[PDB]
Amino acid sequence: IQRNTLNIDKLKIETAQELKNAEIALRTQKTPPGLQHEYAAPADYFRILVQQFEVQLQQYRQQIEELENHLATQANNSHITPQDLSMAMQKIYQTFVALAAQLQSIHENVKVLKEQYL
Amino acid sequence: ENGEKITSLHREVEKVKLDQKRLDQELDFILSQQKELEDLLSPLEELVKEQSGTIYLQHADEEREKTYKLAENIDAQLKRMAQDLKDIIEHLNTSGAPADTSDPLQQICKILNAHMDSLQWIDQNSALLQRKVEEV
Amino acid sequence: AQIKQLLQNPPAGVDPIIWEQAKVDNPDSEKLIPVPMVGFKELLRRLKVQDQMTKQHQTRLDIISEDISELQKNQTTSVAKIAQYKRKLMDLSHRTLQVLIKQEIQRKSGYAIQADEEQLRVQLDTIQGELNAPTQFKGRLNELMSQIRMQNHFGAVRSEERYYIDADLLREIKQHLKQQQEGLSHLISIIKDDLEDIKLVEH
Amino acid sequence: MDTEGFGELLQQAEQLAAETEGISELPHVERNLQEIQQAGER
């Protein structure tokens, strides 16, 4: 359910921007109709989607380049294991531990600032 | 000793149902935003075929429109590509141990990777915050 | 008070010094008061109650279980609406954008249009043939797909066998991952709060 | 025993790696064991 909460917060947030770029759109052109003007939006938002996308392209090549490092691996790829599971989990129980460090790390850091403010 | 657990079971169960209800009716309504915002993107199909008809009774030509038509295809195109990339990744994942996909093994490797990914964030969102503190 | 009301002043014909001491001896006084028990049939008694008790526990536990099933059933096949909604969102976004775009060609020429437009246009040019061309496409996408398949062919056989395996022993390592999952979820929500207790450091 | 958590988890993680149109979130490839330990180490 929990998981289901973030999903709606995402659908929330989104129908809200789309209601609306849909609203920068009707009624703007509704005016037009009578005679007014709404538009250099777009230019805003159009260049906004560009900027949006600009990064998504980088994400694509990042993933692409991972795939082949991965395949690349898969090629090396080819041989038994219970011990390793253990070896993994004793490592995760270390990794979580330094990460916690850092988080308290930060957390206390914030706390310090917050203290300084008042 | 068991009865007590039973209690905070009852508890927390009907607060789960307060949950779902809610999220339930939520989904209706996010859903209704989707029936309205749709009828009326058009009836925005007036207001836009009017402009058209009107614009046609004009001198003529249309222009500098193509660029946009290019922009939308251009914006659209990669969307095409993300799908393909998705269509690859799944195949790669599929290539992986036989005689039993339904075992626990892969279960543990999936879940575990989920953990590893989440841990990653926690890392430098933390490091962020840790990073960020310097200005102060 | 009423506890206080009955527990003192003694019961059934039970001696007052013993009855006292069960009161001091009582391991768990709110949940409990001393109740006189009387030889074997009384233990019989207790057991009858225990059973009485047992059935009702079992049942209520079933009621919680049914409600949980109902929530999960609603939830598990309700993912449908969320996914459907999301796709609808993206299609509406495409139409939104397409309508947004045509309101900027028809009212807007006019043949005014330029200024800011070219900058849009510079960005768009760049991204577009980037992509194109050359490079990317070709090489990469299908050295990867050319490739993937050959690894598929090869992996199958090597497989063959090996020889079962080890699946089996998979149940838990179920179990221990559950517990790592909760630990991570607590750390993530703490980092998120950290930076809260942080924008506020926006000070 | 009767548990349904990691069946949620696995669930999640299953439901995670497959798609979709979501403008951004593309499915991820899952590593495990040898590559993962090192991946954890990095």
Image: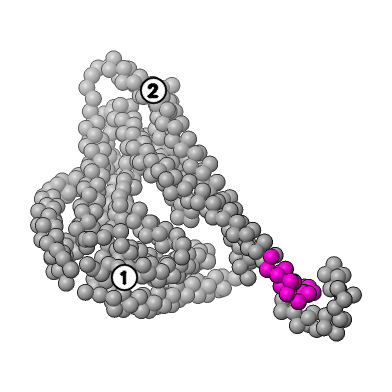
Look at label 2 and name its amino acid.
Answer: Leu
| Label 2 residue SS | loop
Magenta residues, start to end: C31-48
Q: Residues within 10 Å of mark 2 (few under 14, many from 20)?
A: some
> Does residue D33 appear in this view?
yes
- Chain bearing tag 2 is B
Q: Are marks 1 and 2 on the same chain?
A: no
Image height check: is C16 above or below A3?
A: below
Q: Residue at x 38, y 21 (%)?
A: B46
Residue carrying label 2: B47
Q: Residue at x 28, y 33 (%)?
A: C113
Residue carrying label 1: C169
Residue at the extreme front: C41
Instruction: Using the numbered discs, state the Cα–Cα distance from disc 1 to disc 2 in whole angstroms.
Output: 66 Å
Relative depth, front residue between B79 and C115: B79
- Chain bearing tag 1 is C
Q: Residue at x 22, y 22 (%)?
A: B61
| Residue A20 falls left or right of residue C106 | right
Residue at the extreme top: B57
Q: For the N terminus of chain B, which image quadrant?
A: bottom right
Give the colouring mode of the picture.
one colour
| Label 1 residue SS | helix
Relative depth, front residue between C1 and B118: C1
Image coordinates of residue A34 in percent, x first then y, are 43, 21
Relative depth, front residue between C198 and C37: C37
| Residue C29 falls left or right of residue C81 | right
Q: Residue at x 73, y 75 (%)?
A: C40
Image coordinates of residue B76 in percent, x first then y, are 25, 41
